[PDB]
Image: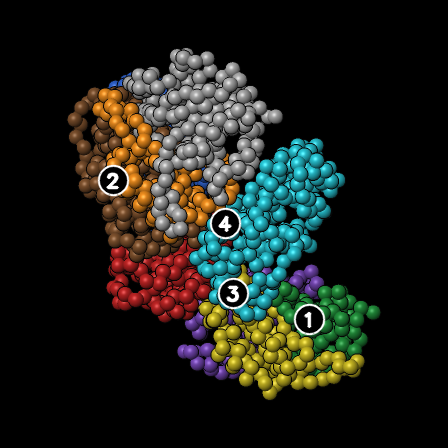
Chain colours: A brown, C blue, D red, E orange, G yellow, H purple, I green, J cyan
């Protein structure tokens, strides 16, 4: 439910396959992702125990030094939130509309690693819910997610998101009461 | 960042609790130190408490104004330490920013 | 059959959700589209009565001023052509080859709003038919459409298209007699 | 099994339709491809007899001079390798893992024409196998392929690939022994 | 640089010794502090130990990964302080870099 | 800035008083810490005193030269911390600069 | 590129075969030419063999070093011709690069 | 420029005449050479004919396409040599360009 | 560079010897080739001799002027090949430059 | 055996004589060096007791402020290593080859002060030996030294050297087993 996670982004798919092989050889982890994404990057995701994933991440970072400037971002979370896993495993269902009075927060970042880190921090701090999470899928390389909750909770999580994301944040918007027509598409 | 102030040992916890419960700081650590300073050209020696205040980059101006508008002594100690944010835990920096209620 | 239409393009999806909410609250319209498109834009489409759609468009433009320079294009048509609607509603069928001697005109523009405006103008002016209409779908953010008719009619519509599109036109080509192998793919 | 092949890349889809029509009219060839691809290009592929395909390629190059600087790349192969055809025709199956000790070579290029030329040269020179071949499909306009064989054979083919691709090569990597988890995704 | 973490007083020396003997840090200083923080909207009060870790600029990523992969609490404290290297003792900075075994 | 040095507990106050009364530092705070370090490949453990020295940017070179020309051990600890001056109390920074007699 | 050397007619094939079988050149063509040159201020006339060597751009330095370290005469003929690669058959250039074993 | 191809000795003149009379080349020179190449890892030896084709810069793409669409072997030899036009006879370069009928 | 001219087989050696002994070229190689060309719209066929002239970059203008001021046919063949000097034997290039007497 | 040392580098020899006079007048020290060196610098070295040398260094730094930007580097060591002194005093002998299996570390820096500081730090940290030490003598103004020891000891000292030298390091190389012919020149 709460394993460790490691994320790497590289400019080359060829170096991505080399990096993934080094990570898999170093420690007994499970490869969640190794594929090219927009706009011509490579995304690698692993999971397992915190010590094994840390060992694999160190080995993968060693190999990436072969490509001068080929590393875009990376992250490592020692214990992922339970709400993050269904969206990463790609097997998920649309959450119900438990409260029509909930506000929404829409966040978009440049990198996948920044999005996963900011979402995990926001979920751990404020009492909010994750409605949507899209990871660089035909949107020009950006990533975005949507959080739901009260107005005070959402503004608290906006503070956490702004701090974690840093200079990789593209935009952040809070909508106090979504319309009925919008609520159908957002809650998906 | 981290802000350092020095207060007499008696008013350490009252100030720290009132600083946190008012949302001006996410966290405070208290250290009993021993202070050597020059008063009227003579080296003195007193026991004080050192306060390490964990606040966000946006709550610093409110914290400084709140401190010297209430600090007992004539020249309050208020030093802000630069924190290297790229090598620090980013999820704790988010915790610091969220628990510093702007109000 | 001929309702009003309003189109907005924005650089941010977060501001897109805010803009869509303001438009829906202002007037009783129907939201046809609110989604991210290539290369990282947001597309919003509404329909209804001319006065209601004009009211919603005014309100949406007010909200877009929050994002400094975030508005890319916009348009508002008081009465859409009947031939445009099946392609916008996404439920359409391949038109038949009513005349093999028809010429074709292929037009591509930078923005979706310019394409819809130019197509509506060309259809209202010259006696031509709309064969295809693709709106920023994995083609690098461009949009394109294909018109069919006689040679004189097609060159008349090319004049209208060049005037309406303006500086948002990328290319324009007239093919006098398509080959049999090409005619299969074009008429789709 | 081994016919001739001709490839053209253009910046405009409108000029792509014009170029394809000229090529089809010149010689009796078969149109394999005419579509827009990322990041806003046009790809045209034909096949047939070497003399007919050469005639069509000459005619198509004449039309492309109308677009000043619109030609990106082109190639013409007089006899394609038998292993290339299933990947170009899009009807292919995942090759079996005939030897777990095989090394892999991952190559990515800027253009489709450079990838097809480099793959054909490498297959003709060294005793290697083609595992995967992706032609500008939602990867930011790049193309890539994967070759498998012994270590000596793979390094021989890397020399051929570097020479043919030239300045259109993006990256090239040799992985001596892929992991079991990686081998599943690579051999696809 | 200098890294600050907070641990309960019982597991201070075991963590510090295991951190140094594994080559992840050249030196550790332990200070007993008093912690004031907000838990469930109420101001609490606990006794902890503050760890000042002297590590090189290259051993920081290994230290951060080692800390939060083993830290007890949900959000570990890990703050890195910027050190002005031009005014510091350069022979000690060499000692810090040499005693931080990369491994 | 703030300079950190570590000395044995016995010579803490004599060094601090002699450092202030000579005008090399405006203020010194003394903290009893517990030190874990590697000596001859074995993890040792000793009790020391941590000195937090408040000096101006101009008195740093004189302070560093004065420290390692008199420090007992072979490699003295001398780390200078960067202070964010724009968010600090500016009237205290003036007090620090004025009480650091250049001489 | 293409490299031109001139050798006496007897040692043409032995040198060519030994050059190809050692992987220093992908291909060699041999042409019997007639040579007119100046020796001791007098115009001489001899029969030789012209070697056209097809090698890659990376195997040129090894080929030149191998030639003049073994060439009989005092000043060996070794001229490299620039090849226009954009108008040449690219699949043959790949064959040349692959058959020139770097070793 | 000058293009070099290698063909078996029997089909040399038929190919050359058909190449000139079709307007694809202004001039062809035929040289009987002796070829040493590696086939199946063994050094072979065959007699061929080397073709030196004089064509203009505009007729090169038509010539290359015409050659490999009709060349017998799997990998045809087609190398284009860069010609220094500023030091060459310019009236012959005009003859080459005029006799290469674009068609 | 290398200059190529074509002459009838009878006047090959007289021209070559007179070209070398006059200092206009360091070296000449003679190859009997077979020429296919178009005369009056009909493909002809004649036997000639190909001259490969080794001259320096400074003796080229004198060589070209000397050739077409004495060449028999109306449009003389004179093509200069670009030589890649960085990968060639530099001591032979010095021999070529020294044996091309400027006069 | 272990006195204090102070080093100053200046762009002008005239200001070097002025600086040396001020240092000598301030405290009872011994002048080890005052001469012009390549590529047009001035080098000053003093020795004595730690308090006297600190007093002289302070006075010398005061005088150097007359020359705007004339100070290049300076250093002050409270207790020099015993192995440094023979190379600074210029009266030294070639160390013996006590172990042919020793590795060597070759370090070159821009300034003399950086070289002396890095050598002293490396000698104090790791168990290594100083073989050679050349201080800006017809090598274009650079300085270099050579250390010898085991492989682990040499890599430990390389870490210390990189930290101390900082941006004044030019190159650093570790040779695991020098050849017999090289060993003669290196050990000199």
Measuring from the top left, give residue J179's x and y in whole percent: 53, 68
Q: Which residue is mark 2?
A: A79
3D distance between C-alphas at marks 2 and 3: 54 Å
Do marks 4 and 3 share a subunit?
Answer: yes
Q: Secondary structure at mark 4?
A: helix
Measuring from the top left, give residue E49's x and y in whole percent: 31, 33
Instruction: Tell me if residue J58 comes above or below residue I41 in the rendering.
Output: above
Q: Which residue is mark 1?
A: I91
Q: A75 or D173, which is in the foreground?
A: A75
Q: Which residue is mark 4?
A: J124
Q: Which residue is mark 3?
A: J98
Measuring from the top left, give residue D173's x and y in whole percent: 40, 58
Q: Residues within 10 Å of mark 3 (few under 14, many from 20)?
A: few
Q: Secondary structure at mark 2?
A: loop
Do marks 2 and 3 share a subunit?
Answer: no
Q: Residues within 10 Å of mark 1 (few under 14, many from 20)?
A: few
For residue A128, which numbered disc appears in the image? none
């Amino acid at each position: 439910a709460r394993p460790a996670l490691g994320v790497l982004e590289l400019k080359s798919y060829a170096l991505g396959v080399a990096v993934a092989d080094a990570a898999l050889r170093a420690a007994p982890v499970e490869l969640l992702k190794c594929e090219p994404v927009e706009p011509g990057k490579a995304l690698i995701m692993i999971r397992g125990e915190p010590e094994a994933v840390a060992r694999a991440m160190a080995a993968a970072l060693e190999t990436a030094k072969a490509g001068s400037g080929n590393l875009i971002d990376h992250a490592f979370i020692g214990r992922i939130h339970p709400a993050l896993l269904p969206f990463l495993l790609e097997e998920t269902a649309a959450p119900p509309i438990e409260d029509p009075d909930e506000a929404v927060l829409v966040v978009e970042t440049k990198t996948v690693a920044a999005a996963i880190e900011a979402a995990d921090a926001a979920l751990d701090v404020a009492p909010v819910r994750l409605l949507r999470m899209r990871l660089s899928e035909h949107i020009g390389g950006k990533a975005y997610f949507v959080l739901a909750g009260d107005e005070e909770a959402v503004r608290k999580a906006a503070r956490a998101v702004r701090a974690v994301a840093g200079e990789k944040l593209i935009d952040l918007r809070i909508i106090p009461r979504p319309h009925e027509a919008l609520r159908g598409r957002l809650f998906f | 960042p981290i802000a350092l102030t020095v207060v007499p040992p008696e008013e350490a916890e009252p100030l720290a609790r009132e600083l946190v419960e008012a949302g001006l700081a996410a966290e405070v650590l208290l250290v009993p130190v021993r202070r050597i300073y020059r008063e009227k050209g003579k080296v003195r020696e007193e026991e004080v408490t050192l306060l390490l205040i964990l606040v966000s980059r946006e709550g610093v101006p409110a914290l400084r104004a709140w401190i010297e508008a209430r600090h007992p002594d004539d020249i309050p100690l208020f030093i802000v330490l630069a924190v290297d944010e790229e090598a620090s835990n980013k999820r704790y920096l988010g915790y610091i920013a969220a628990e510093t209620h702007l109000y």
